[PDB]
Image (cartoon, rainbow over all chains, first blue to last red; front, side, top):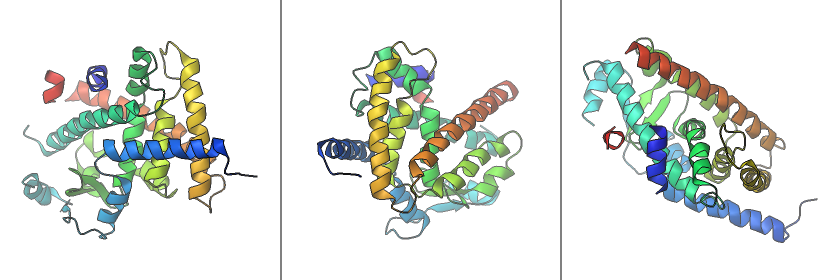
Length: 11
Length: 254
């Protein structure tokens, strides 16, 4: 779920 | 002997670029946190939570106190990962890396940066909360029932020693960039270009610390030793979170 937040914030 | 040559001016422009990007990404800086904690600000005085009654009154400005505080802690962490990800995008060369490696660097990095920067909001008494509007005491956190009572204590112990280095925002902006570009995170595809960015960031950090700290000649070495102790803080922290998940965010849901 850490990845979920990171990937979205990188977009 | 140190010279102001083209190479050093580029390290200073890199330091300025990271500072500017740090100020844009993180609403509450150490400079502002320190002015609040020392009562040298014209800005609103934070509400102090020092006991159960001040917490009830303070929730004004889940059933159990310990679990509501743990929930605030968890939601603020989600926000923090977003701010750190936004800062990471500004580090030269970062967005040029394999996206999978950008995600790995931030996944294994954000906890070390969160506790580095939380030290900026801490003194011996407690921690600034809700962007400097509240202050929660170390002893009040410690008073919460097991296993919540010992959750923040290792971050305070780290902060006491970390804050004695007297880093400012200019120092921290480069230090946090060095942490993010760690070539030793598990499951990186392409290590060499991460270490090449880290090398240049280490050079910029060393120069920063020499110009900014005339009274600690080995501050660079001392700061690297801390990146070592942050690893251990994050290990204990992850372990305590596994324990709590086995024993007890709007954006996550979406």
